[PDB]
Image (cartoon, coloured by chain):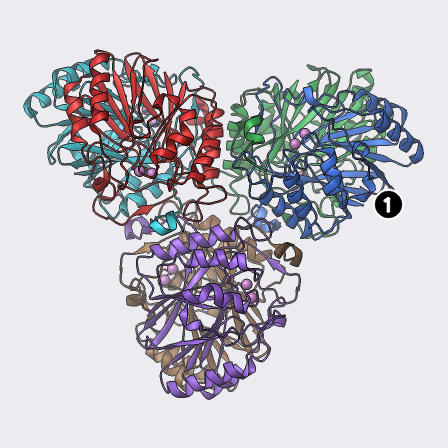
Chain colours: A brown, B purple, C cyan, D red, E green, F blue
Amino acid sequence: MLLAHISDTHFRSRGEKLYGFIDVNAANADVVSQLNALRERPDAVVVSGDIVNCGRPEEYQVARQILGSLNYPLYLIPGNHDDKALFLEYLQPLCPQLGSDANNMRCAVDDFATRLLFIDSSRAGTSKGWLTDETISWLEAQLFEGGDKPATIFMHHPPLPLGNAQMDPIACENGHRLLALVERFPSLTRIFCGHNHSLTMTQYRQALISTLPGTVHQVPYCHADTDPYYDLSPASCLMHRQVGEQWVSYQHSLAHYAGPWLYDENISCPT
Amino acid sequence: MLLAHISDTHFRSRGEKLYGFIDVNAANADVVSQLNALRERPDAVVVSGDIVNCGRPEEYQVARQILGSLNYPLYLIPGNHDDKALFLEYLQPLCPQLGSDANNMRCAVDDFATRLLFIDSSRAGTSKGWLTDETISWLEAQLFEGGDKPATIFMHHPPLPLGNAQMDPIACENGHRLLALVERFPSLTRIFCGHNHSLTMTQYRQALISTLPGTVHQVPYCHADTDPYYDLSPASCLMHRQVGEQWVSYQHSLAHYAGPWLYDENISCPT
Amino acid sequence: MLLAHISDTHFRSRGEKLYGFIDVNAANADVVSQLNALRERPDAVVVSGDIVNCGRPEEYQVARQILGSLNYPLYLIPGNHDDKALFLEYLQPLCPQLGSDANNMRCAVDDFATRLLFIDSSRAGTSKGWLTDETISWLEAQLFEGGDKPATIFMHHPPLPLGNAQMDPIACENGHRLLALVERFPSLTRIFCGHNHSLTMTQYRQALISTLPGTVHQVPYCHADTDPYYDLSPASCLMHRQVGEQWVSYQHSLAHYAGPWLYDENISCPT
Amino acid sequence: MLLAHISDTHFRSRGEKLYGFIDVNAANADVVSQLNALRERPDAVVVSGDIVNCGRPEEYQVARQILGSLNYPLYLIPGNHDDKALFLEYLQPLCPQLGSDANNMRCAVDDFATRLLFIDSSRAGTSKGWLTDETISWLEAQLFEGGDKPATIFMHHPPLPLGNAQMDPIACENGHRLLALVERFPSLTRIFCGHNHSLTMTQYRQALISTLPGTVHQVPYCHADTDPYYDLSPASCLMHRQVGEQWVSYQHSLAHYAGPWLYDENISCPTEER
Amino acid sequence: MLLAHISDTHFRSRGEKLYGFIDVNAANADVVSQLNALRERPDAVVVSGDIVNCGRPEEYQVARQILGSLNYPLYLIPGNHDDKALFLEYLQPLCPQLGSDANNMRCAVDDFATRLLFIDSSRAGTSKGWLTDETISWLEAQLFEGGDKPATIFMHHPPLPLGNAQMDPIACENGHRLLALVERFPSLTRIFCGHNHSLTMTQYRQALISTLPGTVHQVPYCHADTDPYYDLSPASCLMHRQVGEQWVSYQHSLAHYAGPWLYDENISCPTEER
Amino acid sequence: MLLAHISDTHFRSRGEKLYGFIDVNAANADVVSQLNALRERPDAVVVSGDIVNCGRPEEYQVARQILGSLNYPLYLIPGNHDDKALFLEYLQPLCPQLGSDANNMRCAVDDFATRLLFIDSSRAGTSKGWLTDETISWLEAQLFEGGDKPATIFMHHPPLPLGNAQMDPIACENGHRLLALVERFPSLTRIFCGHNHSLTMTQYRQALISTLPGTVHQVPYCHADTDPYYDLSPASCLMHRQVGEQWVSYQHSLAHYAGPWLYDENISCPT
Ligand SMILES: [Co+2]
Ligand SMILES: [Co+2]
Ligand SMILES: [Co+2]
Ligand SMILES: [Co+2]
Ligand SMILES: [Co+2]
Ligand SMILES: [Co+2]
Ligand SMILES: [Co+2]
Ligand SMILES: [Co+2]
Ligand SMILES: [Co+2]
Ligand SMILES: [Co+2]
Ligand SMILES: [Co+2]
Ligand SMILES: [Co+2]
């Protein structure tokens, strides 16, 4: 298993820029072509929510064009910036397991050594996350049924506070429900999130829990300052690899940079 | 607790550049001034190994000058590129807990809600890591006496393979001795490493285990390809914060980038 | 009093770029977000003319939306690139004190220790500036009424030759009439202008007279060469502050640059 | 008269970078080559103090090499980071008009329509400026003898506070003495200063008073915050030109940027577009 | 004679970017203004094919506007990404000497010491080049009538393989027909081509044969790897100059870069340094 | 045959920069590592003169270390900036085929399908090129020796004027002697030169004649202007490849740039 995992694309409508000046559409199209050009090719691409910025049909038309040009199987989940019904309308042909109920989108993938669980933590009319009873029951059923096989969950909102003054108030509101699932099921070992536009990682019992950077604009972590900052610090994605019994995640830069070159001992330490 | 954690500085001697072209001395002096300018100031700065590139006295002269200009308490550990005896000579006044035995450098910090354990996984004559009997014994004693107080270990070499073709052959060779300690001591929940010049994270039982990017040059993760690449993809460090019961780590960019600006809902979704 | 003073925005219609390649609309949206994000917030933003590039209705639609997203009271005046009627129609709601006569747009502001006088020096069918009889009488009356209260005038066109080969022929054609006002009224101590896309400054009796850089492209100063050049040298604005009895202007960069860091005596001069 | 005017070069010793990471020596060598390559060549180059960073003889060796490669007559004055004796020992050959007394370095230039007065406002032991009695007396003598001929003063420290929280406490401490000269002598119409690493301008009676950007690093203007910031925002110099009866100053970017191109009416307002 | 020669502009529809992220329309607008701003002004500009990306009418609307804004006579030829009928409809008014037959667009220019020959090697339904009987027969007639006077051919597709694994399979399929004319006619001493988005040159008998860089995106030369790579490595055009008896071609960067400065002996080899 | 061909490296002594601000030493060390990292490995690397800037011993020290770290056989020739005796002393161990006479450095290589002839056109006391009686006699002998086997000459100075106002006066002054050999010997079909810091190409009879870009700073071609300009427009090398009967040269960028990506029909022309 190799997954390429990106988040928070924030597509805008045709010929608009984010905030009038960040060309998210072009930036994301570069990202798509970079993923398409990888020498070690992913088995699939994950996009963990906030696919569009404003929930508009015209933004989804751009998302479908750019995401649909990815040359991989896609696993897509909504964020709070998404509109559930439009997300299904425009993206279900790119991820057929999202199904037909805008309010119960979720799916499991059993192709690999670890089970993958994709859920919707977004809730209409708020930035905060919410896990419904049906999502929780479905999770319990999948973890129960999976038995001994490890599982990873992908969701938009972090299920616990991370100390980030901007982002904490809008985390997953009843995230304790999912934390109760990591207590009950030892096989649940990864929870990966979007929303925070930052690589922020913590550990609860046996599960590693981590947010991801955005594909374009980032949000700095502040512990006290609640001013709503964003910036254009370097974007990246996370690569997830099955390595024996270990699930290993590593950061892959989406910036254009100098190199690579080859290490040579004579060049490293000249005489 | 707020820690700024940087790694793999690879200082060169005065007026020399890494590989003849990467100005590590200047990039590191920038980094130092960046850390000195932080608005939310860390309590301490960790540097997790490969302080110098060639283990030369004249490189430690530079390292002492630049690291010596950080306005913070420092916790310094060696890597495989370091010379243990010069490390003590030139850096012990900056981290006095390193003591006077070049072959037994380690120390524990009890100032915070989580215990900090700093060790030397480096071995002379090899790039591979090695945990000595003295080190493993000291670790067991710390963890036994710590009781239910959480513990974090900082070491140069990762204690398990991560699937990185370049890096796995030179991980910590007897790292299973540390994995045995994670098994035995549930309070051991974080292990942070240098060496890989990449943010690569995994989980073993209750312990989150992660390598850090370098402060200057980076090493791409490859699964198959053994060619020894390095590049100038974006540099960063890790900030570690105690957030109630959770240790939270987040990535802090050391690049110069555009912004911050302030999110405004009108600008975000114009009419 | 703190004023942020920008000039010569040259907005184009939606999705268009200046000369087909300079993204003025994006650059200006970035500027507006910079101004909104200032820690020391100005009391008002001045925009001294050439708001649009071609005087077209769709350019004004973009200007109204982008300038309308500034979180400040605005003072707007036209330049030669503007169209007076459309300027009034689209922009007057953002600056109502201009009145409702497109041919006599001007205003006095008395909120601060120094009186602010905003006038229209643009003339239909020409790049040249022109001061109407009405504007001059209004100016004389304002300056009589004001007595020993200091006054600053903002206008598009500079009142006198500056030796700039490209710009001098298209300065204020009857600028002598404003210079006459400077001789007669010791209270008139500042004249700030757009048009030249350059920080150019001179003194006539008690008055400091300065043109401003543009927000995007700049015009180099050449003494002999009349080739009509432009460039993308760095953009800035002037901040104007009342410091006791002094009106102080300082340049504020609108470029994205490395820093800031903190000065440290021992880093500056190491031993 | 055309003058190129740069300030606060802050040269470091050979093979040293400012703060360990800003290559001030390389940046200044680029600036010198930029000034040498100008199509419209200045009559002289002014450098208004803080020529070196630490007052060290090794920094003066570098300053002398780099400023000595300028293909122009130089007018140099010190700043607080300069050491008076070393400044004269190393730089007097580049600007012999300053004399041979390190405590009284100044000169007047009468070649042009406006008289140019260069003074040392620096004072040993402090960052603050200070006008000595001999400087003040020399100034009064020049201004008296100049009569109706306009005059421009170049000095390191600004002679009045400008609202800059970091820089104001270290302005010219007896600046009021020079402001009294502005009142007395109507032909004194320009005072140009370094020190602030910022283009900050104001007017006091008939005199325009402006500080300059540095050639490398800059200092942001902050009204309340005393935190000693600096940054690498774009560097520039000031060009000063006599245009008829007007002294005109314009900013000349020292950054490397795209262009120039030529304006074309058809390209500006295309018949195809909204 | 001075010609500025650009190639492979790949214009897109108004508001569209190439592959969604390369702003070819803006990049080409910058290039046009760069050409308009040249101090040493060319006598004409050559554009050697792949004018639009997808052969669509909306792309030709953009090409016509931007190429239309060049302040020079234009010599335009198609590439495989062009549609011949639309190319003629939209661009013939910019290069009327092509004629009125979309299937037989070529022209010869006799203004200079060397004859210029512009031909269309593109063929509908394929990326490969193809020299038609009409084209070869007209080339022969031009070369034969030309007698002594040297000749230069401008065509989209290279007429021989160049060892480029990506590009060779889509060269001029019957390029041998043009190599046969090189053999027959010692007058024919240059053939310049687009298609490859690379400066690649070779020599066949008396003729120098060269492909050009693109104005925006480039294509790396690979000898074995057939992965279809492209990149944003530096763009440039070729300038062609008659220099007495020699035709001289030189690379002109279209990138925005630092400089120029002026060389100085004192600065090149300082007396202070090793 | 694959040759990587660079030129005009202009090395300075350790710690020095060209003109005080162009870091030739780092730029060239970057180039050397780029060449070492090439996927399609050249058979050899040619460096066609002006190896050092000032002809000083400490410059040759830097050149020897940096060029010595190329993992390829080298063919090195001097330019006018080089000193013949010091060139031999420091660089002849890197290219022993040159011989042991400083005033007669040259060699012929028969390894490939095209013979390679390396000559010294530099002359003490001048920037102009000169072919000595010995050099010209040797070339004649070698062209007799090659018979119908093709030949390529590498030299520093171009043997004919190219209309470049700065460079023509200091071309190879008796270059006509080489043009005479082209006429006599039809297998001589390439002449490659340094000196001009420009890709400028022409054809004389059967011989293609081309100057190369430098590795760092470039010289613009001007027809009339003799002002001695240099700039930092993009650097490159030429790769020379034997392709059946054709010698093919192609430009290889030494800049760091975005990409590569993979072309995709549906991304190129969306529907
Ligand atoms: Co988001
Ligand atoms: Co969100
Ligand atoms: Co390391
Ligand atoms: Co290591
Ligand atoms: Co304007
Ligand atoms: Co105007
Ligand atoms: Co200073
Ligand atoms: Co100072
Ligand atoms: Co093409
Ligand atoms: Co083509
Ligand atoms: Co050279
Ligand atoms: Co040369």
Residue D173 in the figure: left or right of residue E148: left
- What percent of the width, then of the height, locates residue A4? 53, 64
Q: Evaluate whether residue A267 shows in this view.
A: yes
Q: Amino acid at mark 1?
A: Asp
Residue sitting at x 62%, y 70%: B126
Q: Secondary structure at mark 1?
A: loop
Q: Say which of D151 and B206 sits in front.
A: D151
Q: Position of residue B194 (x, y in %)?
A: 51, 67
Displayed-image quarter of ligand 3: bottom right
Chain that bears disc 1? F
Report x, y in % for residue E269. Answer: 58, 31
Check the picture and name the quadrant holding the N terminus of chain B: bottom left
Q: In the image as oriented, which residue stretches furthest toward the front?
A: D101
- One can see residue C196 in this view: no
Q: Which residue is mark 1?
A: F111
- Residue D58's image quarter? top left
Give the total number of marks visible in the rendering: 1
Q: Residue at x 63, y 59 (%)?
A: A39
Percent x, y for residue D73? Answer: 42, 21
| In the rendered image, the vertical position of residue D15 relative to residue E257, given as above or below | below
